[PDB]
Amino acid sequence: EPLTKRLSKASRKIHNVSNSLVNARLIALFSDKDLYAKALGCFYYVFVALEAALDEALKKGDADVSKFKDVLKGGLYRAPGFKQDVQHYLGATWQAQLGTKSQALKDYEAHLASLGRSSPALLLAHVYTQHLAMASGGQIVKRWARKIFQLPDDVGTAAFDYTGESNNTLRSAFKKQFDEWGAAQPQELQDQLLSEHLAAFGHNNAIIKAFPLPAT
Image (cartoon, rainbow, N blue to C red; front, side, top):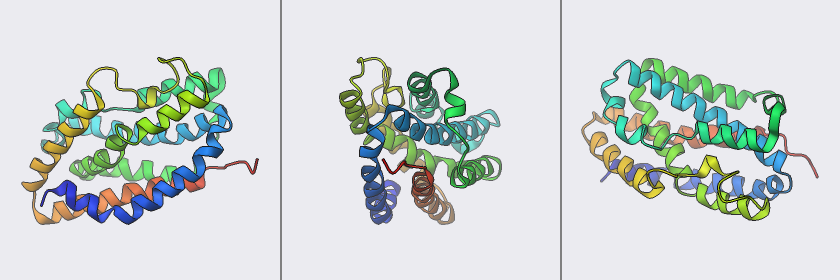
């Protein structure tokens, strides 16, 4: 049984929980592009943290992360796309409008940094969870944003855009390598990857719930 299938089976229940959480907040976010962009800003920081940790592992020549260099550095990365969208919607004072980071966000940032220092291979479980969802379900958020905010075809959804390598190719290439590499790892590390996959959902849900949504 491939690692991807073991992880996706284990995360089925929390994925459904996340799904409800996100959909329940979409209508609220789409009511105001500023609200939407502030919410994007949370995950701007998530992806800054994850991608900085990965870049650090690649620079150190981590045996495991380096094996993934081509699939990681070929269009999967999201932080520049998120930053483009946040600057687009919020303008000159975007950084102030993002407010203060929730404890939930700071905790995930700290966790990712710690993984980068002590066990960089476990970052790949968070890539599996975070980056591949952007390439997937993220396309639905993108379509709604463009419809409701009446966006030009080349502005406003850079967080969800894949203008070089296709989202489909990036996702399948990472999956294939993740499964091949994962199967060659000790059972303890495979279990840790499962745990970190679940943790990414947990962190994301915490960050989503901590976001201050106006009653209006």
